[PDB]
Image: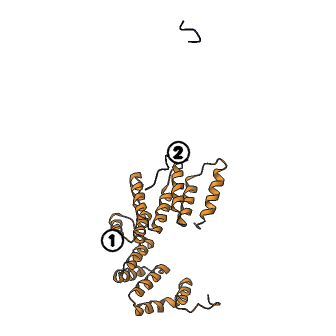
Amino acid sequence: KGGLHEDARKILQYMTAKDVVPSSKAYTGVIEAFGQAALYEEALVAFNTMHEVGSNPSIETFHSLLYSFARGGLFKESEVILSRLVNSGIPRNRDTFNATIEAYKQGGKFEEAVKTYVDMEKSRCDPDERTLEAVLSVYSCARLVDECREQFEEMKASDILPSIMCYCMMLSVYGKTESWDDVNELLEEMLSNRVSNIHQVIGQMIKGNYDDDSNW
Amino acid sequence: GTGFNKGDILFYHREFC
């Protein structure tokens, strides 16, 4: 969880040196630890070692692999893992769908990203805030202000206390087209933010009010 | 007569591709 790949590797080597067969959960943990630091080869080696010792992969292992590959944009590995899942027969939860969405988003395949989005909407499962966050990010990246603003006004109507991600993505997309009026009108409601402190701090610091040594 | 003189590595480790 903390992305301490070196410590996880040290613990794995220590527990292997004492004739202890590692469990599937421990291997999943070390795999996700290696994937945090973009060390894909070590994560794949650990995943391969899982089968050697008999510790079969679980759904958590596939989720960790999908997230690690999606962060780096390795969508070929994403589709390989999806094929592995489909031939394994494991049901695909929202994690698989949104991991695929963000993998295609980071890989730049916007059209295939929205194709997978509508494929997910067709079958089942309710998209969480993460799925709409991913679709908003992929829309903002591919120079689409209209879809971004539509999704922004649709999602904020659910009284969900919109997160930092949506505000930063909106600021980015508005700065793409030099929509200084939109940036200012978002900042006016962003500055106060009576509910949370993180939004207030980031909104004050982006404008330059916190650049001082005592204010940083 | 005939009785004389008493008569797995490299697996689960393939290239991921």
Chain hosting mark 2 = B
Q: Position of residue A13 (x, y in %)?
A: 63, 54
Q: Which residue is mark 1?
A: A111
The kind of residue tagged 1 is Glu
Q: Which residue is mark 2?
A: B9
Chain hosting mark 1 = A
From the viewer's perspective, is residue A164 above or below residue A98?
below
| Chain letter, colour orange in render | A
Q: Is residue A180 left or right of residue A197?
A: left
**Residue A194's image quarter?**
bottom right
Which color is chain B depicted in?
purple
> Split into 4 quadrants, where in the image is the N terminus of chain A?
bottom right
Q: Secondary structure at mark 2?
A: loop
The kind of residue tagged 2 is Ile
> Split into 4 quadrants, where in the image is the C terminus of chain A?
bottom right
Q: Position of residue A183 (x, y in %)?
A: 43, 90
Q: Residues within 10 Å of mark 1 (few under 14, many from 20)?
A: few
Q: Say which mark, if any, is on residue A199.
A: none
Q: Residue at x 36, y 72 (%)?
A: A110
Q: Position of residue A101 (x, y in %)?
A: 40, 68
**Residue A198's image quarter?**
bottom right
Q: Secondary structure at mark 1?
A: helix
Q: Is residue A5 visible?
A: yes
